[PDB]
Image 1 (cartoon, protein in one colour):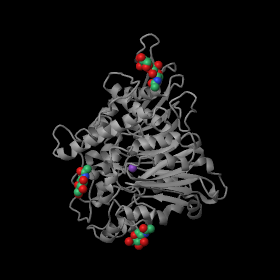
Image 2: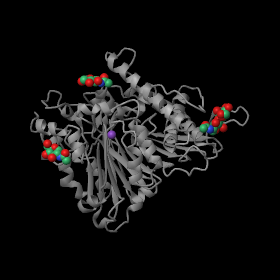
Image 3: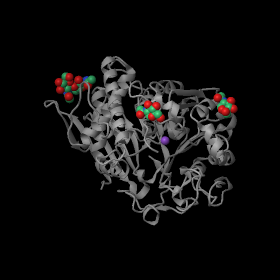
Length: 180
Length: 344
Ligand SMILES: *[C@@H]1O[C@H](CO)[C@@H](O[C@@H]2O[C@H](CO)[C@@H](O)[C@H](O)[C@H]2NC(C)=O)[C@H](O)[C@H]1NC(C)=O
Ligand SMILES: *[C@@H]1O[C@H](CO)[C@@H](O)[C@H](O)[C@H]1NC(C)=O
Ligand SMILES: *[C@@H]1O[C@H](CO)[C@@H](O)[C@H](O)[C@H]1NC(C)=O
Ligand code: NA
């Protein structure tokens, strides 16, 4: 049940030095996000989100995911419920497919983590890492627990990754011999 | 999804529009503006990426478009329609190692690219063979209002299937024909052939044809009527399947099919209808938006966006007044009668 407007910032505490969400606009923060929900009136919500370039881009990516999650929690929950809640759930028939998909996604995620470690100087893998940090921060935030990874991190194959891979799954499904 | 890239008469403007086809249950929508400060590489000496600013049509918890439609501060507009793959012999190219999933490849290309060539170059690396799309990359930096064809750089077409990515600059073709339409069918004959579409043309006919499918045909017939932003909205919203001969499905009973339009309304197909293949059935699926931009609008990181199934010439979709009232659609309006809005 989203409010018209919600603004959250993620500050890195000078002392802690821990990340904490605050309400409102704080341009000193690592990131801030503003969700305006006009779905009832226009069929759209609007998000704008900024990260602070005075922090490195890893922390920015993570924080970007965190702040998006914090201003859109209800929308995330509902979208998840509408779209992917049951996908490979606890009670799936297609356990053959779902196990293959979990294996695939875990191996894929591990392969990228490995490539990032093996290629700390790579622009490409750097951009991949930022993308996954953003994903990680989004999931962490929604879960209510902020852990900024400085090295390798684990993405849940069937967590918020599921919201990103809907188009990928259209082909993963047949490639992993799901019936149809 | 449908897309149209329209060169206005006299090259007055270049309009770029995309209409997502999706399950209606996906209709919690967020238009997202990201203002990031990422660098190209893991060191502070690295330049800021070309694509730090981006507006895109999206969904809750979805850290990319999914549609896709993006306006990037690098002057690029990236959009796709999905081609998929019907050749099972290509699936061996879908591997957990050596394949970066499409959504990440998309985000990364969007971030690093300053032009269509580099977008294609970045995106095609570690081709996963998943979310197999035709991507259109419009570089508005290469667009001169009123100017003649610059020969290159305005339009880059990329088509991905497993094990194969084909890329061409299609500026000349855009300027010559005055449009680029996209409608879920690969344009590159090598991609069309490699992904098993010939067999489906052979079995089902024109629907799988690049040039003869209903949308190709409607675009061929009607694209020139897009003379401005609202005309673009209108063609992108287009569904008049009951009365449009181009919406006739000859193997179907009844013959008018709501799938056979620019903006599908599969919900309006009869449940007891007889249909040669699943796309044509009654479904809680169809066009669920239009997003449109222009040279000036892209420049200001801005778009016209309309949310919901088309209601220009079809009754407005309304969950409670639909075969799909029991489907989960939390947070979603019941009645979908929304007009385009400037965003923002
Ligand atoms: C970017 O910034 C963060 C924050 O300053 C760095 O993370 C700190 O790293 C030290 C040593 O790695 C840790 O002990 C601190 O606990 C980290 N702080 C936080 C907030 O977690 C980080 O190393 C920098 N670089 C990268 C690549 O992330
Ligand atoms: C799926 O089945 C095919 C045979 O149709 C087989 O060759 C292939 O190894 C299988 N792929 C996976 C990943 O299960
Ligand atoms: C594609 O397939 C068609 C039908 O078999 C054939 O006529 C054509 O030569 C092929 N084209 C290419 C470029 O592969
Ligand atoms: Na798509």
